[PDB]
Length: 289
Length: 267
Image (cartoon, rainbow over all chains, first blue to last red; front, side):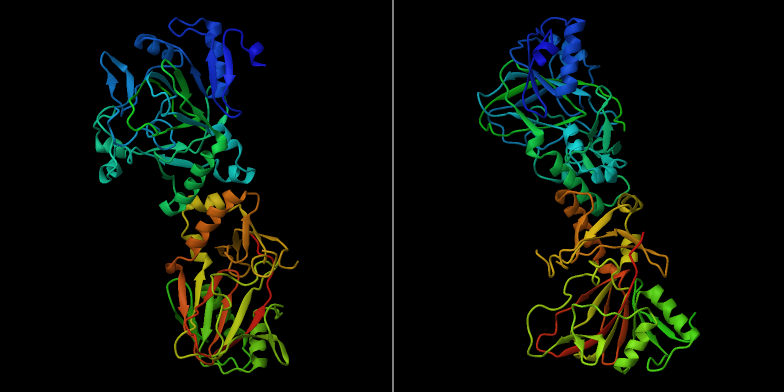
């Protein structure tokens, strides 16, 4: 049992798939070795972890994030004044543009080395509205048939940011506001990288599916017609409701998600309401089989 | 080359018109060998102006292999081997073989070939489409080929004359088959008899089979055969699919067919 497994923290799982609330820790202070090791263990098991009532400074946010690995900010997001490491998920009450992250994805997979983790802090959030969905890509992989696993385990996938800030984004109508989103170079948006379809997590050693509808373009070597149905099945499979959890935000909630083995989704159900969270990005290494 | 027959290909994919031979007479070794060569290359072959009897029809068919026939279709009186593709001028409704398929793939050993003979056909209307499953396989990307080559598919007649006993009986064929005569690899799926990819869930199997149906039935993999009276046609039941065109409402259409037995589809 978790009450006896963990001696320095208290862990309350959110679902039988992923997610856990962590209490009995003060993120304003440096964490001792035993407390940190328990947090990391919980992170590896539960994949998305959150800490209610953590009224921390920007510096304390950065210091906590550094325990997971180096700070490596994502290309697209604006940073707060004085803190280049601390980026914004900010939506004004009156704005009606495209919602950041309103499709199932994981962050910045177009990079050669996408983020390992993101640490998100609720600054000012609605009483209700603006939950974040998460899902386990371990579970998504583990629930495929043995035959389907054998069929796809050797495949590689082409990723790019073309639909987010590349040529395909610039061709369409649904645009982000300048609140949290930078103006970007089109060539950076179109730059392709190839990642494995199934990846091994370097911390847990576990295999997970690695595909997302936002950044994945096609299966490497296949035509668009060949790739489209296989990728579409995998999106529908991974995003099955039974593979998900739903996180409700409160002021001063600090959340860490694993950017390799989870996907996440914004919920745009708070029109007319201010929503502001900050985030630091933990650098990762090249996704590997 | 062709020294004993004249061969006119119909498209750059499949189909050929063969002339310079009389199918009423027995074929010598040299002529037969050339016909078989053309059959292996062109997959669907047709011979205009062959006013052959029922007996001559059977005799020609026997050169390709054993002549069965299949239990589903109705035989003409006096000739169990010779079966009817008949639609009266008064008749209207749903036509035999109006989706892309190949014959009786629910069997452990489906037919190798079918020999069709036009008796009374309209001036226009009632063409038969054919497509090459060699071409279907060959035009898949090397990556897609490698991905699906080891898959097997469950076939049954359950949607045709089963629950959805003999119709419910399942058989398993490879998704990609090697032709026992030509040695060439071809895709082997059809929407009429294929149920699922063996080992996969419904959600996994459905979109993959659906893509393969769409791919195989691409217009550029097809040919279209127009019928005339006394036209004799042979199709390869392993490496082709075919489709009847129901564009002859109110017109009489009559053809006979013999069925050549095959062996287990093999990788």
